[PDB]
Amino acid sequence: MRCIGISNRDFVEGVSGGSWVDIVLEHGSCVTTMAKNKPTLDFELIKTEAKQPATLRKYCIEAKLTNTTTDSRCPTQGEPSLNEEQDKRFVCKHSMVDRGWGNGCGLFGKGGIVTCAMFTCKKNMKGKVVQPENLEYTIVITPHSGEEKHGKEIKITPQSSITEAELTGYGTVTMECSPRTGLDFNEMVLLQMENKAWLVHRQWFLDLPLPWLPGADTQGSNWIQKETLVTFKNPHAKKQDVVVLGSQEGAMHTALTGATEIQMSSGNLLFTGHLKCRLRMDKLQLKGMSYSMCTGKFKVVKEIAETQHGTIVIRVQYEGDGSPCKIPFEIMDLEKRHVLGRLITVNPIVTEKDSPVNIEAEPPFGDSYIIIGVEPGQLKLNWFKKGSSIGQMIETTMRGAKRMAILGDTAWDFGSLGGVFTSIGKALHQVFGAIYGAAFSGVSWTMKILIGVIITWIGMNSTSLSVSLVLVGVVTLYLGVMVQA
Amino acid sequence: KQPATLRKYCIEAKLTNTTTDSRCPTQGEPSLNEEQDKRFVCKHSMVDR
Amino acid sequence: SVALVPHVGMGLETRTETWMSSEGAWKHAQRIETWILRHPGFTIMAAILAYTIGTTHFQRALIFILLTAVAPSMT
Amino acid sequence: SVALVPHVGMGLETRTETWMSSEGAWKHAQRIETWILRHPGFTIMAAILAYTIGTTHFQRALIFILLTAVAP
Amino acid sequence: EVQLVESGAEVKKPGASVKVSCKASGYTFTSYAMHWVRQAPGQRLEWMGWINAGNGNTKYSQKFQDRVTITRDTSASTAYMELSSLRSEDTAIYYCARDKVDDYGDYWFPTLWYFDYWGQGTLVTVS
Amino acid sequence: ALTQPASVSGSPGQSITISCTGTSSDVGGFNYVSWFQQHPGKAPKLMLYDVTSRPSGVSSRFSGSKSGNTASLTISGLQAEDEADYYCSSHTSRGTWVFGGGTKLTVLA
Ligand SMILES: *[C@@H]1O[C@H](CO)[C@@H](O)[C@H](O)[C@H]1NC(C)=O
Ligand SMILES: *[C@@H]1O[C@H](CO)[C@@H](O)[C@H](O)[C@H]1NC(C)=O
């Protein structure tokens, strides 16, 4: 029941011949899995943890300059020279300055000069890389028991593809996942600030134009391309002075717009990404399947409520005899002839007489009837639901398109049953995503919108080429409008 | 000789006394007495309930 | 600096909101529109240039938009 | 941010050098070249689009350069 | 099973500082939030505040914002706190309570069955 | 704060109702309403949270209900051991917790 109330909630229907189904888990999302004569389970990825990160490169933010020295070089007698340039802690640069008799030199002309000042960094960031074998995925498992540590927590590691979770009264669920098919961590990097952290690309991280050392260093003083953080100024070509630039942490924050917020102050914790998983529901069984239904009177304790997905939830208390027993619950039309709505809290059972049980399902569009109990004493609160079948279909297509756009090829496996057309979609969408990523790498959403408009205009005034161009233009316009950045 | 301060631009800031107020759906957005207190920066978002 | 090379649209976006989703989608629109409203002469000159080099209306508008986008970005 | 709106080209430059004169003279060109090198697919696509849209070689090159410059 | 151990009673002069602690045993201390509720003799219950044992966030009541500081100790599974600027009315019996944190380790929304267990109580006397 | 009667007394084996009234920000706004028993010299214990529901290990005689801005606790079949202090607690939308004024339950001899 933990998935109830989440806006990003999806349902998967049916099982394969092997009683398995392919599902994808997301941080902040939850998927409800139901099947014929099978218990309904909620899957939600709640924790992503990384163990033993390796420091790769530290970029500096706070720097101070001391021991500034300049030496007075005359023209045509070569460049000047200082003792401190022997050590790379001193940033130095050669410029050209005026010299003359007023400067106590025998000839008039443009003379050399060098300024050297020690580079001392005060505050720096850390870039850590975790191997994919150290990933830790935590998934919570909760069935629709109807009870008001109720769920089951499991640990997913690359060390064990198959993880077994025992459910009290529901049998044991066989859980199969691929931790390394989601976020590509060996290509990834974890950036650390003073107290914040970001999950950002490794290559862009190496492309940061800031002083840095490789993570293996222990001295922490041999910074590289220190010129990017200092500046030499020649106001009148009389001499140069070196001054350190300001704090780049604000500039870094303005540079991490598209990065994802992750917390690793106390252990590397991640709350983003996706996980493709193969669900095996072979050994699951309905809790309380071997129980007759309740023939006593039923009482509703919480008023019926509607979720954002059109489903309904109700809490009922039992006061007859025969506990534990099944609740006879079903959906009728206004005609009392057809059954229209079907349960998603399949096989509701009351465990204790005085303990209320939450029954949660979905009604049909328009008006219907909610039936609890049996003659005599069936509860009669009918319904009212806003919406339409066409609206539901278009909204479902919008959700599917958004999921495909934000996942990639793995979205075809979100509810795949191993069909041949599913594999065809795998291959084609994977290759088209390959070209799309190779073509649209590093551009903002406005760039995608502009290119889409251009391609649409090219297509509309061009033929199979014209329709292909307008199709790719409209799909990339959708991608640009639906992407955050 | 005579400089006049036009305006002061803040470049480092610190935030304390963080507050949060929530409302059930279809009851508008919550309000706090620091919302008028313009020393307190405020923003309204939407949260699953 | 690093602010000129933000990690934008590199294919790592997920379902969770990123660091600067909301107004990070738009600091473009705001700074380009402020630049337009502050330096209208360059916009006018770009308009004549687009009318000159551009032969069809579509390419005229395209060149004008690209020049107007470069003008603050190139700075 | 402020780095996106530098105090450049406002008609106040004089003989003495500015703040980020030497370093900032070519930094934009350097970052554009690095982006081009590290994102070749977009450059190829922009070249194709400039080839298709224009009517003469001059505006082919012009559209290519503009599209390449705006993207970063 | 679940047991909470509090420190012994202390008597101090008004205006001083008193430090007490509550130990959590029989359950995961890190995945639970520690609350503190005091009750003066013959008075009502008052919510002093709470501390998160997962990350360290602390929230205090307005009446004790500048007088109560709460710390933690993950290794010993015991929470430390100190109350300063004592007054005559501060004489009360303090109870520590537990509450499950969310799956993300935060305490934005308490669970339905919060305050399921309470400590034995520690008396602070001001004279 | 939360306002509840100072003391409520009733005959043993009878049904009595105790009401806790707060504001729309804590009691009427949210369902985080709980009740506790304060024995003399003993720590408080929880017997009812989320008034529509009950905790484990608690007899079903205690029943809770909410009427708008007022939360009511109903006990059927009063017994001798029920004589103790009672408190009502609610969690407001500001993130703080409020408690009632304390009510002592008396069982007639
Ligand atoms: C730089 O100057 C400081 C203070 O004058 C001095 O302590 C330090 O030794 C100098 N640096 C070197 C390398 O001597
Ligand atoms: C903010 O918190 C500090 C820390 O205790 C406190 O001293 C101050 O009075 C608080 N101010 C407000 C307006 O809450």
Image: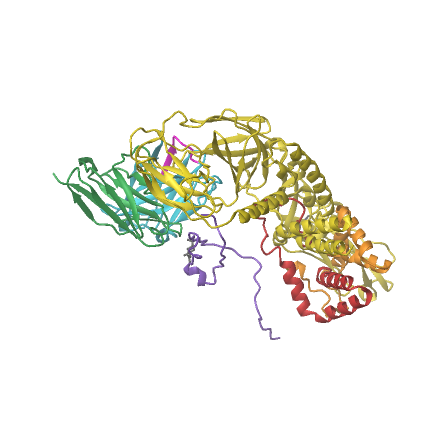
Chain colours: A yellow, B purple, C red, D orange, E cyan, F green
User: Residue E51, percent across and down?
Assistant: 41, 43
Q: Quadrant of the N terminus of chain E?
A: top left
Q: Nearer the viewer, residue A451 or A88?
A: A451
Q: In this view, does A453 lie above or below A298?
A: below
| Residue A82 seen by the camera | no
Q: Residue at x 29, y 33 (%)?
A: A320
Is residue E24 part of the magenta span, yes or no?
yes
User: Residue F2, percent across and down?
Assistant: 29, 51
| Residue E57 seen by the camera | yes
Q: Residue at x 78, y 61 (%)?
A: C59
Is residue F81 part of the magenta span, yes or no?
no
Q: In this view, does A169 lie to the left or right of D27?
A: left
Q: In this view, does C20 lie above or below B5?
A: above
Q: Is residue A227 left or right of residue A140?
A: right
Q: In this view, does A169 lie to the left or right of A118?
A: left
Q: Which of A91 and C49 is in front in this view?
A: C49
Q: Which of A261 and A13 is in front in this view?
A: A13
User: Which residue ends up furthest to the left in the rendered image?
Assistant: F109
User: Residue D16, percent across and down?
Assistant: 75, 67
Q: In this view, does E46 lie above or below C54?
A: above
Q: Which of A144 and C9 is in front in this view?
A: A144
- Ligand 2, seen in the image, is in the quarter at bottom left
User: Residue A168, percent across and down?
Assistant: 43, 27
Bounds of the magenta segment: E21-29
Count of numbered badges drawn on the protein: 0
